[PDB]
Image (cartoon, rainbow, N blue to C red; front, top):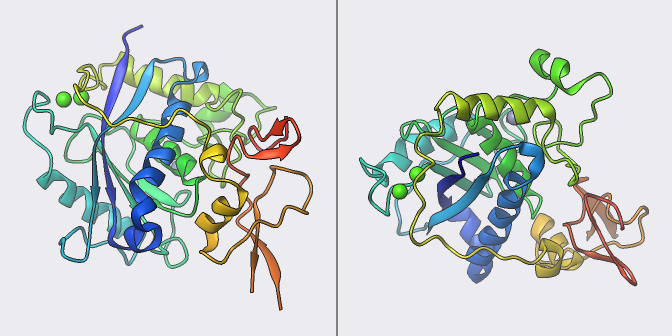
Length: 290
Ligand SMILES: [Ca+2]
Ligand SMILES: [Ca+2]
Ligand SMILES: [Zn+2]
């Protein structure tokens, strides 16, 4: 089976910078790594290799895309912007196959949105339309990412009419292309339905532009995200610099609860990052302490 490469542009926005500071590039790489690990899983049934060839960080001095107010607007804004950066032929190292915008603007509290982001379906090799938006809110934005790129590869939600047929009645929502905020089974990240829709896409020659290998991609961390950022840090990434992990809430791994201000524990209900210590000889995998 012919091996694919997705030459990804990554764009961090004006507010993503304020939030992450110097820690940004590393953060963004840690997330992208994590998305890339999902596309590399045998469950997708295709040798797809997610790869960052460019990374751009804006100001505040750098006239970027007009992000906000909505998610639908942000995507049309981004996709028109991102083109001024691309090149005519996939022969120039600067040519990228798809683009992703991470923003820390609350779009999904003012506007409708897919998970915490948006994308069109089946666009991988259309430079005018191959692009995505993700609202960042922690390491788990690596799955928001994959879900949106999934759509880029012509995937649909696992609760659509076509997907019920293929996944079977006893299907769970523990996969990347589930319409809810996901808790992806890492033994089986992609469902049968997602596995098929991509196969058909690539087989019908829609991934013709993913065949060239980029000469110099950015290095992606090979350590777990829970080792790179501990529980407190992960909490800090979701909610703010003052947020500490509330470990006391059972079961370990299933939900990252973080402190806030009397005093409280809050949650976005997305698991602890994979490889967070949760026991003496234990770390978390897919929201469980194994
Ligand atoms: Ca190229
Ligand atoms: Ca390419
Ligand atoms: Zn979706």
